[PDB]
Image (cartoon, rainbow, N blue to C red):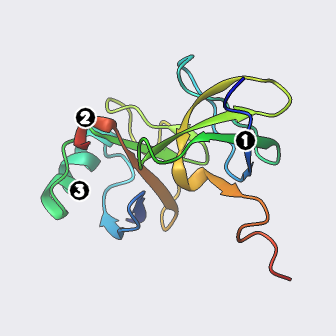
Amino acid sequence: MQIFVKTLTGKTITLEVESSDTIDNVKSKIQDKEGIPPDQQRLIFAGKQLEDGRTLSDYNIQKESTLHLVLRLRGG
Amino acid sequence: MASKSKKRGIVQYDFMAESQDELTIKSGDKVYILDDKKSKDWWMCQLVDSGKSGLVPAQFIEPVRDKKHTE
């Protein structure tokens, strides 16, 4: 599916990922797409911060939704 | 208190903070912008009622008067 992962910098990218993919693998996909360190990436959906070891299903995230990607102070 | 100029913002996104350094911001409440230039991604906000201060995502806080009412 496609989820709209919107970085805090305003870079809204449409990410193609499986509903059963881990947030870890999602970060890998974004690390391929834009090239961002997974640890630095904090995905927040509806106010829920997503853990690496959990999937899109663990937080009940439907496709074609907008997730906010807030980066750590790792890149600053 | 020297930081008496509390710039007012409104929290749009309901964000539950797990760490104490992070601020649990309930959607629809009021927050004070402590620092907004120290960092770009995470800002310092303080809950108006709860009095709790902490780090929150920049685009989760929308300053009042600024762009919330031009009508």
C-alpha separation, residue under disc 2 versus residue under disc 1: 35 Å
Quadrant showing the N terminus of chain B: top right
Chain under numbered label 3? A
Residue A61 visible from this viewpoint: no
Q: Nearer the viewer, residue A40 or A43?
A: A40
Q: Which mark is residue A39?
A: 2
Which element type, helix, strand or loop, lies under badge 3?
A: helix
Quadrant showing the C terminus of chain B: bottom right
In the orientation shown, which residue stands out farthest toward the bottom?
B71
- Frontmost of labels 3 and 1 is 1
The residue that appears at 81% across and 24% down in the rendered structure is B50
In the rendered image, residues at marks 3 and 2 fall on the same chain: yes
C-alpha separation, residue under disc 3 versus residue under disc 1: 39 Å
Left or right placement of residue B58 versus residue A38 in this view = right
Check disc 1 and report the residue beneath it.
B5
Labelled pair 2, 1 in contact (Cβ < 8 Å): no
Residue B26: x and y in percent read 75, 38
Quadrant of residue B33 within the rendered picture: top right
Check disc 3 and report the residue beneath it.
A30
C-alpha separation, residue under disc 3 versus residue under disc 2: 12 Å
Labelled pair 3, 2 in contact (Cβ < 8 Å): no
Q: Identity of the amino acid at label 1?
A: Ser
What crowding class fits label 1: few (fewer than 14 Cα within 10 Å), some (14-19), or many (20 or more)? few
Q: Which mark is residue B54?
A: none
Labelled pair 3, 1 in contact (Cβ < 8 Å): no
In the orientation shown, which residue stands out farthest toward the front?
B2
Chain under numbered label 1? B
In the rendered image, residues at marks 2 and 1 fall on the same chain: no
